[PDB]
Length: 31
Image (tube, rainbow, N blue to C red; front, side):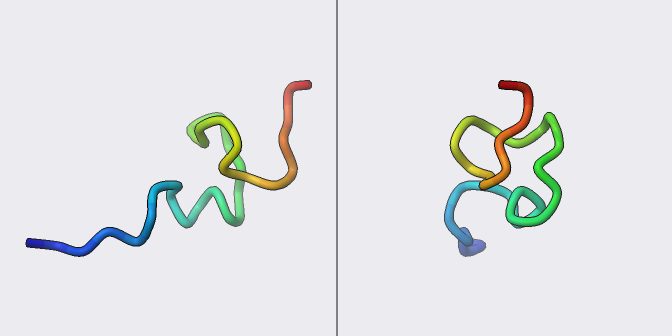
């Protein structure tokens, strides 16, 4: 099987777009 990085998409480390779940990204947007 394939290995998992962790949980939050790496993209969340960079672009915290609306697809990013709660508490994944640093710069939390929308309140």
